[PDB]
Image (spheres, coloured by chain):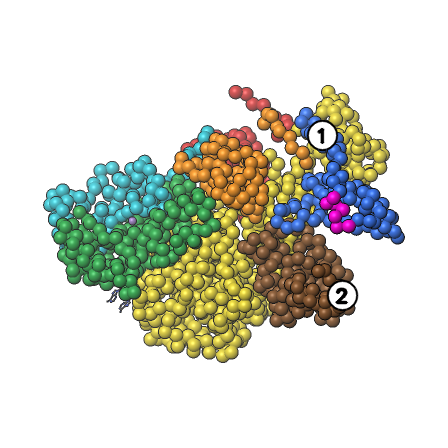
Chain colours: A yellow, B brown, C blue, D green, E cyan, F orange, G red
């Protein structure tokens, strides 16, 4: 009736049933990296990797691919449906990236389902390949800063619930920022892939800040800090092919851990950059299914396989199998059209502005929202300027948001770089900028620019340590007890941690599933579009327990816009009430029913004196009506309870019109 | 109340499927219905604790003769026994044997009984042996 | 059940109706009432035929055999339907 | 005159004895003899992989004395990589499009190629920024043609199996859907 | 009233005005390959190509690109609108 | 439920689960409807003829059966998915 | 042409992009609050109405000095980008 929040309300399309692979009953899952890890630990896996002549693949289809293309909206139901085939058909992947990034709060917040459930369900369905997550070192998957014991508990849970490889990064390449997360992953027995974010352009010796020696020194520190695998996270797709060959080549001479490269295909050169990385001996690369690859996402796994099959160094992927998995995503992606708004061509301006993949689409949105859709080019130019203003920083969540927030702010207020320097003490900067300069997201390389810091801080005193080291530990016992009161029953450890990470959305989620049940079970078209008249769906509550539901008709609205919806559920007719929030011949009394209270005369309604549900006695006033301006008061014909109301103040009425119903 | 049979797959449809499910529930036994595509709305499917589509792709009568898929479902659901009702597979030697192979109780007589009373001649031979009158 | 869709693929059976009495005659009276008391609309049923069988005095007697039905053509004569209801609704439908 | 050889098969697979490098080389010689000024290589299905391109172009440069003009489609996602190899083998001219009208069943991005090569030993002569400006126009204009923008627009590596050229894939899916075979599109591809 | 043949009949969206490059009055178009051809013929162009160390580019935006992506529907009006900027901004294309 | 012909008078989509629902494959219009309610038909028989940028197609009976309701008339504009005819088994 | 208030009312109009007096929804969502009345006098940047997009609020500002004319939406109204919301005469 009311449409789904945030999209154009339109009829549910007719969709193709997705192509699922036929897995003969009793086919066995081959063991893969999860078995090695379970048996011989992190170092066993590391040793195995060193032995591999072929390039290994991590598949980001279940996390980063759709974060970049479909605003992280891919729902669990669609993920669980293909998971079994992934275990059988793609058993040689190093890992499946399937958790972390934005999936944590998006699940709760926009999908109304539980990411822990996603993780645990998948864990059973895919027992043979390691699971991988993206963790911001400082704050995990959260929206702010949290005390160390929180970060530690999150990681502990994640590891237990089935995450095996934690790719840990810091938004400014500040190693201190990650130390807790890294240690907690070590403590939990799982693999640490600490990552260096790539930025700038090491082939341009004009640019003396983020040079190959910078990257090499940072590698050495991270091995020293005890990572098992070295992540290179090229979040904006800036690493060109000849730079990748040198960078990887030189890192292989410098450190003695395997290297894991992650890029985006934003510029259209991702495959080529992966080809170079592979010639330089990189160990593992990040790819997605074709249909969820390209543009701001990862390069195609199957495209890489074929780009390399006739070279000196290959991937271990079964092409045909990956093609079969891909058919599923080709079909499923249609469901998410309302979120498939990324431009989806190459975009080489990234080499100038350096906005990471997601933020480009995201920040265009805020610009359009705020009336700047016509000046999107200025905003991009300003992003570049602001990055220079900050001393040239690494831009990825959350550092990227700061540069974005200021870039918008300055275009909106017609402010130049010079204007900021001149009038900065009298300008109130966005909170993210103040927070940045206070050191609340850590310390930039080369430090903050002094003049601009003073003018934003306005007397305030920076910190120079991890914002989280100075925070009061959380009392879990106390929080748990607070949450139990709020929820009305005993929460799980995971509930608690989620509450702490995201208190407002966690409770909004609970409200939502108390009212509507675990809507996670719904097929995605129904989740987003409801049902057409005459349509029948099947809702799988649980293995073997299916609701067969048919929409028969939608009733006419009463005064407050309530409509009766007429369904059949498992052959049972069911009528449910839904308030129509946006309503764009009037009913006569059934003369035989004395519960029907009718207009006596032609006129209008001055005032309705009662509400649905109110209790009334014979002679009590129900409403007041007018006839050539001479008022009358329609009385209750007997004792009872007021039911439906068919008119509103002002409404024109004619004699016989049904006005109100009063149940005995 | 029962010994081994905690859950029963009813390998049938319609009236007799419902009949068996009612008996099961009265004995605190859990039930599994199966249904063909074409019986997706059949009301026997609503009377079980669980239900599964059977015979995807097959013609309608064949769907409830799909031995392999029925067994898969029984195994995947943890059924201890299968009641075949009447018609369909209730007199099928292969199906009964196949229950045996999987350690699933077939609610009926032994395979050899189905064999001996399947061909009219060996039944008549058995009547004669049992010394009871027969038709010329 | 009310709302079901009978298909052509399987048996047509809607419901098995059984009646009991201390005597066959007592059980027979009940079968007659119950068959008449059923209301089923939207499809045709075999009830008119069952009634003919159950009312036939050969049935009541208890003396019938394999050939009874096949050699009793009265069983295949059916009263004209009274569908005054349905006609009345067509009229109301049409003016409306 | 740019007479062209259509590329097909896979010259790196000597199982496949029909459309081999010698076939391509002999056909080049004939066309020079027939008097083309430039030799076109038309890879209409995007089947020319990168290592094959290097050899094919490399060898053709040793065989004929006309410039070579390579045309591919980015259907598989490897078009740029294939262009990079071609360029290392000394190809003279390649076919590109504006970014916003590039990728998938179209040509590789001109501006993407420029940046893939700018730090190598052999470059393109393109002004990046100017091409980016022209590209903004197409980014905006393309929205007008949404009702015709029904090409799938991801990589599609099955082309190496079925060998349907770029246009015909979309086109033939249409006829299949039209004729009631939308559910059996995979069978049609196999056929 | 009746919609355009072959597509879903829907309301005209509200479109962004396309970003056109600002070409100052009196800017001159650089000569490129058409001049070489006009002066020295096919063999002059061929000879020119042989001397080029850089890889040359042919741009298919106006034909093959939209044949592949947009069923060849790109209309002349949209093509003429950008053509002048193409002459000024992309003068080094082979073709 | 009774049927009444309305002498003096949103477009419904196929229920994808029901194969008795015959749907438009493509966007266009209906040139000609070749059958009537009640008619008896065989797999492959012509039901109606539709147009897509003027190139005609003939929608065939998916199986043997009896033609039920008809939701379109000659001339009618149609979009892919639209329910056109129903063919009972 | 004369104006008459329809006391009992029972497709939404898009901005004419050429007319900058037409103030249009930037994004798809709903209207939380309309802050002005027909006839009110306003200055560049002044608040006209507040709109929602996946619950993240935005304030539509006057593009210039002027006089508020017609209003096409009410509190609660669902809106799509391009929808004409308010007109502000110069
Ligand atoms: N001398 C040669 N021998 C054989 N084939 C040649 C070649 N030069 C170029 N190619 C072919 O062209 C592709 C890209 O050459 P490019 O230098 O553009 O791009 C290369 C280059 O940037 C770098 N790379 C690979 N091997 C290298 C080496 N030995 N020295 C320097 N850079 C290398 O990685 C990219 C991918 O190399 P890949 O072989 O995967 O892909 C190569 C290969 O297929
Ligand atoms: Mn990433
Ligand atoms: Mn072509």
Residue F60 on the magenta segment = no
Q: Residue at x 16, y 56 (%)?
A: D29
Query: Viewed as shown, does residue D32 lie left or right of A576?
Result: left
User: In the image, residue D4 lies at what x, y percent?
Assistant: 22, 51
Query: Viewed as shown, does residue C40 lie left or right of D188?
Result: right
Q: For the residue labelled by badge 2, is the local secondary structure a helix, a strand or a loop?
A: loop
Instruction: Tell me if mark 1 has few (under 14), some (14-19) or many (20+) residues whose alpha carbon lies within 10 angstroms of its own.
Output: few
Q: Residue at x 42, y 37 (%)?
A: F56
What is the magenta range?
A: C65-71
Q: Is residue F56 above or below residue E68?
A: above
Query: Viewed as shown, does residue G71 lie left or right of D87?
Result: right
Q: Is residue G37 visible?
A: yes
Q: Camera-side residue: A403 or D1? A: D1
Q: Are marks 2 and 1 in contact (CB under 8 Å)?
A: no
Confirm or reject: label 2 Cβ below 8 Å from ligand 2.
no
User: In the image, residue F38 lies at what x, y percent?
Assistant: 58, 36
Q: Is residue F19 above or below residue F2?
A: below
| Residue holding disc 1 | C87
User: In the image, residue A228 lies at what x, y percent?
Assistant: 45, 75
User: In the image, residue A651 lies at what x, y percent?
Assistant: 68, 29
| Residue holding disc 2 | B132
Q: Main secondary structure of the magenta part?
A: loop
Q: For the residue labelled by badge 1, is the local secondary structure a helix, a strand or a loop?
A: helix
Query: Viewed as shown, does residue A638 lie left or right of A470?
Result: right
The subunit letter for the residue under badge 1 reads C
Q: Residue at x 71, y 56 (%)?
A: B16
Residue C67 on the magenta segment = yes
């Amino acid at each position: 009736v009311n449409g789904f929040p945030g999209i154009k309300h339109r009829d549910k399309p007719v969709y193709a049933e997705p192509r699922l692979p036929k897995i003969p009953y009793g086919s066995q899952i081959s063991p893969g990296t999860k078995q090695i890890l379970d048996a011989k630990g992190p170092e066993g896996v590391v040793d195995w990797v060193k032995k591999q002549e072929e390039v290994l693949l991590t598949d980001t289809t279940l996390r980063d691919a759709h974060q970049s293309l479909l605003a992280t909206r891919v729902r669990s139901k669609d993920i669980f449906q293909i998971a079994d085939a992934m275990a059988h058909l793609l058993p040689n992947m190093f890992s499946f990236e399937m958790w972390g990034g934005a999936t944590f709060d998006v699940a709760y917040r926009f999908l109304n389902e539980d990411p822990w459930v996603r993780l645990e369900t998948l864990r059973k369905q895919i027992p043979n390949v390691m699971f991988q997550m993206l963790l911001r070192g400082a704050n995990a998957v959260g929206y702010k800063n949290y005390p160390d014991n929180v970060i530690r508990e999150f990681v502990k849970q994640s590891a237990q619930s089935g995450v095996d490889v934690f790719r840990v990064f810091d938004s400014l390449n500040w190693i201190k920022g990650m130390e807790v997360s890294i240690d907690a992953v070590r403590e939990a027995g799982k693999i640490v892939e600490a990552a260096i974010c790539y930025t700038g352009d090491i082939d341009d010796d004009t640019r003396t800040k983020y040079t190959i020696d910078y990257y090499k020194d940072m590698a050495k520190e991270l091995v020293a800090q005890g990572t098992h695998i070295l992540g290179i996270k090229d979040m904006a797709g800036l690493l060109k092919p000849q730079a990748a060959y040198r960078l990887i080549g030189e890192l292989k001479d410098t450190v003695d851990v395997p290297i894991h490269l992650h890029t985006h295909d934003t510029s259209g050169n991702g495959i080529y950059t992966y080809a170079a990385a592979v010639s330089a001996g990189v160990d593992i690369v990040d790819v997605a299914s074709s249909a969820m690859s390209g543009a701001t996402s990862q390069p195609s796994m199957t495209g890489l396989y074929y780009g390399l099959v006739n070279g000196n160094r290959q991937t271990n992927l079964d092409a045909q199998n990956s093609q079969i998995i891909n058919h599923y995503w080709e079909d499923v992606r249609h469901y998410y059209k309302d979120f498939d708004n990324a431009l989806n061509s190459p975009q080489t301006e990234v080499y100038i502005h350096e906005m990471p993949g997601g933020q480009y689409t995201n920040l265009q949105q805020q610009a359009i929202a705020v009336g700047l859709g016509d000046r999107w080019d200025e905003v991009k130019e300003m992003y570049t300027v602001v990055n220079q203003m900050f001393g040239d920083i690494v831009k990825v969540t959350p550092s990227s948001k700061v540069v974005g927030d200021l870039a918008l702010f300055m275009v909106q207020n017609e402010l130049s770089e010079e204007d900021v320097y001149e009038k900065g003490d009298t300008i109130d900067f966005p909170d993210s900028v103040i927070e940045f300069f206070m050191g609340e997201i850590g310390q930039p390389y080369g430090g903050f620019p002094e003049k601009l810091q003073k003018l934003v801080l306005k007397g305030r005193t920076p910190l120079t340590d991890r914002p989280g080291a100075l925070m009061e530990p959380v009392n879990f016992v106390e929080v748990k007890a607070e949450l139990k009161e709020k929820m009305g029953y005993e929460p799980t450890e995971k509930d608690v941690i989620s509450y702490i990470l995201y208190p407002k959305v966690f409770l909004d989620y609970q409200e939502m599933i108390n009212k509507y049940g675990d809507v996670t079970v719904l097929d995605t078209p129904t989740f987003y579009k409801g049902m057409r008249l005459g349509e029948t769906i099947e809702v799988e509550l649980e293995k073997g327990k299916i609701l067969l539901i048919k929409l028969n008709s939608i009733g006419e609205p009463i005064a407050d816009g309530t409509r009766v919806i007429y369904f059949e559920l498992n052959g049972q007719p069911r009528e449910i009430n839904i308030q129509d929030m946006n309503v764009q011949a009037r009913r006569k009394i059934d003369t035989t029913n004395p519960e029907h209270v009718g207009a006596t005369m032609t006129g209008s309604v001055i005032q309705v004196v009662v509400k649905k549900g109110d209790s009334v006695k014979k002679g009590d006033p129900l409403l007041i009506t007018e006839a050539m301006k001479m008022e009358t008061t329609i009385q209750a014909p007997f004792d009872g309870e007021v039911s439906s109301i068919y008119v509103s103040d002002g409404d024109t009425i004619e004699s016989g019109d049904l006005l109100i119903e009063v149940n005995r | 109340m029962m010994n081994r049979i905690k859950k029963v797959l009813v390998a049938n449809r319609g009236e007799i499927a419902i009949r068996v499910m009612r008996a099961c529930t009265e004995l605190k036994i859990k039930t599994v219905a199966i249904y063909s595509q074409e019986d997706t709305g059949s009301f026997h499917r609503y009377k079980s604790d669980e239900a599964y589509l059977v015979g995807a792709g097959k013609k309608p009568i064949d769907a409830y003769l799909d031995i392999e898929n029925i067994i898969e479902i029984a195994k995947e659901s943890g059924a201890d026994a299968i009641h075949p009702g009447y018609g369909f597979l209730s007199e099928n030697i292969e199906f009964a044997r196949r229950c045996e192979q999987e350690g699933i109780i077939f609610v009926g007589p032994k395979s050899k009984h189905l064999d001996m009373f399947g061909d009219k001649i060996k039944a008549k031979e058995q009547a004669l042996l049992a010394d009871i009158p027969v038709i010329p | 059940f009310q709302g079901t869709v009978v298909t052509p693929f399987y048996d047509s059976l809607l419901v098995k109706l059984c009646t009991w009495g201390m005597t066959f005659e007592q059980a027979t009276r009940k079968m007659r009432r119950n068959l008449i008391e059923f209301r089923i609309r939207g499809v045709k049923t075999n009830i008119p035929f069952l009634l003919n069988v159950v009312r036939h005095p050969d049935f009541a007697s208890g003396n019938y055999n394999t050939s009874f039905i096949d050699t009793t053509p009265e069983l295949f004569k059916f009263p004209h339907i009274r569908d005054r209801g349905t006609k009345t609704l067509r009229y109301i439908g049409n003016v409306t």
